Image (cartoon, rainbow, N blue to C red; front, top):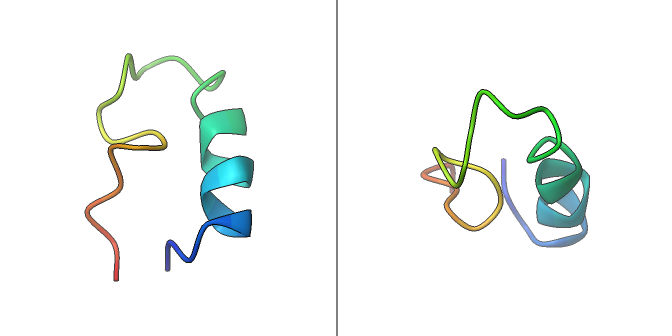
Length: 31
């Protein structure tokens, strides 16, 4: 998944905060 216009969308999923970097984004364990 995470090529880093995706990690911009997942640091955006970072304010989906279940995470404080678990795994959002960094910290993505995806590709």
